[PDB]
Structures are given as structure tokens and as C-alpha cells.
Image 1 (tube, rainbow, N blue to C red):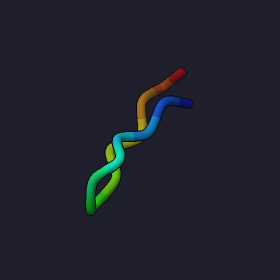
Image 2 (image 1 turned 60 degrees about the horizontal axis):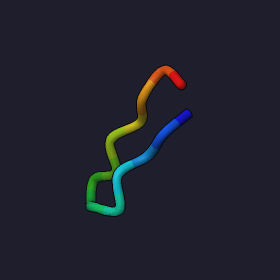
Image 3 (image 1 turned 180 degrees about the vertical axis):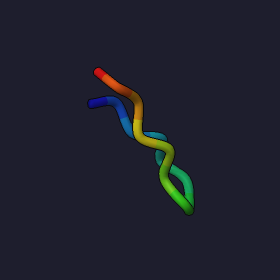
Image 4 (image 1 turned 120 degrees about the vertical axis):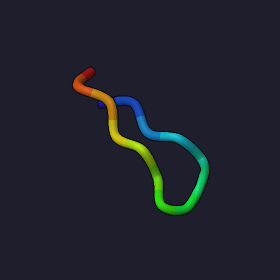
Length: 14
């Protein structure tokens, strides 16, 4: 469910 504070935001499985 993790997401990077970037664009495009990378979404992780957690």
C-alpha cells in the first residue's frame, strides 16, 4: 500500500 511521493507515484503491494 506504500506510495512514493513522486509523479507518477509508485504503488507498492503493501
